[PDB]
Amino acid sequence: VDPRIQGELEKLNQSTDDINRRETELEDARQKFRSVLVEATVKLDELVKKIGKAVEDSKPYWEARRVARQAQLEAQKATQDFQRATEVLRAAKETISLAEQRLLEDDKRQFDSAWQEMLNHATQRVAEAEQTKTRSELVHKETAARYNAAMGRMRQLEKKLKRAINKSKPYFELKAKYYVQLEQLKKTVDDLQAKLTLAKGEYKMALKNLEMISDEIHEAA
């Protein structure tokens, strides 16, 4: 059946012509990635060759800053986890203290069937609430120490290398501007090719639809 195959032919023909774009749109994005990559390294080398001692001397400071960025997130999460651990023990103390007066000696005996049901639930949680609160608190002592200790090294190094630091700041930022640009080009290249794989994939599926259709026509009469 001449129409049966021509329906897959043009379905295959449109898919393979789309690939010719994708192969260029990838190669173009790939080459531009190469071009920015090589310019990034040569403009940064000239900046090192001028005055590059400041760069190596600044590395102990920037590492001491890298350590600090970590310790401050650790301290913040320990801060927020301690803020939660206090709020549970409080709600457990408020629940118990409020329920204590009503039930003790049963001077009031109102909803006395229901009050303990909340008090005993509270009684059980306090055992764990006090465990976990002391836990997060002690960890908060560790992290807040590590935090304000990592700052002390960075600050003292800032005093000890402030000259080298102020000269390497333009170097790191032109490196960062180029990085994020390269990061931008790296992202565009990576998904543009996977887009082609799904394009090539849908092309190869046509060659099987034809391998079967021609086989379906053949097994007729």
Image (tube, rainbow, N blue to C red):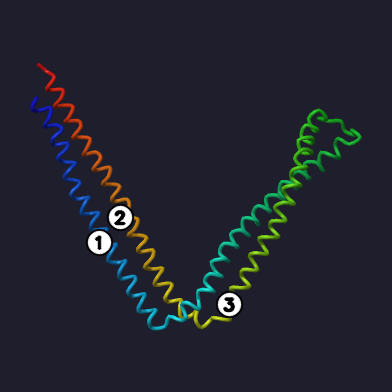
* Viewer-nearest residue: 87 or 48: 48
- Give SS at disc 2: helix
Instruction: Tell me the crowding category of disc 2: few under 14, some 14 to 19, or many 20 or more residues within 10 angstroms, Cα based.
Output: many
- Which of the two labelled residues, at mark 3 and mark 2, occupies the earlier sequence position? 3
Give the spatial CA distance, label 1 vs label 2.
Answer: 10 Å
Give the spatial CA distance, label 1 vs label 3.
Answer: 42 Å
Examine the rendered structure and indicate whether residue 63 appears above or below residue 200: below
The quadrant holding residue 174 is bottom left
Which mark is drawn over residue 31? 1
Give the spatial CA distance, label 3 vs label 2.
Answer: 40 Å
* Viewer-nearest residue: 29 or 94: 29
x, y percent for residue 206: 19, 35
Q: Residue lying at the far left in this picture: please name it.
A: 2
The quadrant holding residue 121 is top right
Q: Which residue is mark 3?
A: 157
x, y percent for residue 218: 12, 22
- Which of the two labelled residues, at mark 1 and mark 3, occupies the earlier sequence position? 1
Q: How many marks?
A: 3
x, y percent for residue 163: 51, 83
Q: Which residue is mark 2?
A: 189
- Give SS at disc 3: helix
Q: Amino acid at mark 3?
A: Leu
Instruction: Tell me the crowding category of disc 3: few under 14, some 14 to 19, or many 20 or more residues within 10 angstroms, Cα based.
Output: some
Q: Amino acid at mark 2?
A: Val
Residue at x-position 32% and y-position 74%: 42
Q: Amino acid at mark 1?
A: Gln
